[PDB]
Image (cartoon, grey):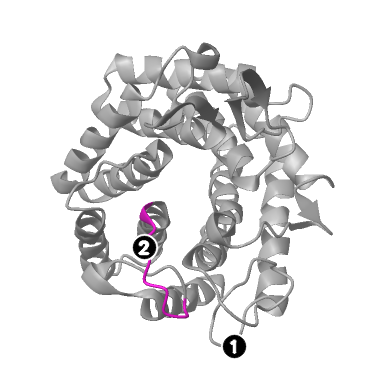
Amino acid sequence: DWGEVAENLQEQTYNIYLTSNGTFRQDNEGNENFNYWWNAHMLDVLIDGYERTGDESYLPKMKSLLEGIEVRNGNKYENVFIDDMEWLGIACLRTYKLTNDQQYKEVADLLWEETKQGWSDVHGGGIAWKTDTPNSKNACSNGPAAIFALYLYEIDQDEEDLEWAKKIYHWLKDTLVDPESGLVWDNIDYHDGEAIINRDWIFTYNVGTYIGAANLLHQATGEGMYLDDAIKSASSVVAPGELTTGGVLKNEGQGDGGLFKGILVRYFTQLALNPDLPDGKRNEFEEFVLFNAETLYHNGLTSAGLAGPNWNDEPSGRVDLSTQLSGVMLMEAKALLE
């Protein structure tokens, strides 16, 4: 069953990438480089496993990871990459909602304060990409920020957190979202004195976090406009276009790009579980997840359980942790859809 596929990928990922301090190394060829936001998504994958199985063995692995991230980041959680902080904050609030472990909440609160400090009037709003790159406002430092704020609002029910979610999402939609397709451009930045939007870089995980934010805003407010937003973006993901090759989410390389597919699948799946989704869209989205899962399972996984950047070809060399996490995420999402 899909659950057993996901469990096997979980075990393989853990054993191949485990390294010092309960964190996870950059690749399977001995590169020990610490990648903060990849390890945040490893936390996300471990939570996926815990939620599926209820197996208590996930909990020490999660906790060690949380603490190891702090150590390998220089004995602090703050990072000059603001998107990094947002991703870890999301994982921490997910875990808090599931375990009530206050250590995760305290980390998330620190990171939320860091995140808000990244907002500025450059380009009319939005959270900066990095604390030393204030003039770049990126989909990956805003979509996740809106999700982070929505999890915080769901938990502490402080209205200022929903205010923040709405502010962030409104700026994102106005600036970086194509009004017709709902695809999401990577960033707006100043280059040689002038403001440029990179429309060439349409990445899976940016439309993914836009969908995720839209879906959570729908759940936080009830307003159908958010669900319509989510549906338009997701429908453009399913239909043939820039993000698919033969009905399969495209190869976006390794390194950071290796993780992009998995993040889209995560939030795509959360949309498909939205109770107010029309039945036809639900069936279509579930089918899309199944088709990608089948394709990776039969054509992309090496015998040892490693997924490559192209879910249709087995990798023959280095596999970065990010790439592998995307495969694990797809399988956990399929299992979640039963």
Q: Check residue 33 for magenta coloring.
A: yes
Which residue is found at the position 66% from the left and 44% from the top? 203
Q: Could you tell whether 105 is left or right of 171 in the image?
A: left
x, y percent for residue 290:
68, 61
Kindly identify which numbered label has been placed on residue 171: none
Residue 190's image quarter? top right
Q: Secondary structure at mark 2?
A: helix
How many numbered marks are there? Answer: 2
User: Of helix, strand and loop, which mostly describes the magenta segment?
Assistant: loop
Q: Residue flagged by tag 2: what amino acid is it? A: Leu
Identify the residue under disc 2.
Answer: 46
- Against 117, residue 272 (above or below) is below
Q: Could you tell whether 70 is left or right of 28 in the image?
A: left
Judge the density around disc 1: few (<14), some (14-19), many (≥20) Cα neighbours within 10 Å.
few
Kindly identify which numbered label has been placed on residue 303: 1
Q: Secondary structure at mark 1?
A: loop
x, y percent for residue 75:
17, 52
Give the magenta-colored segment's residue range.
28-36
Which residue is found at the position 25% from the left and 72% from the top? 20
Q: Nearer the viewer, residue 315 or 235?
A: 315
Q: Check residue 178 for magenta coloring.
A: no
- Farthest front residue? 192
Q: Is residue 338 visible?
A: no
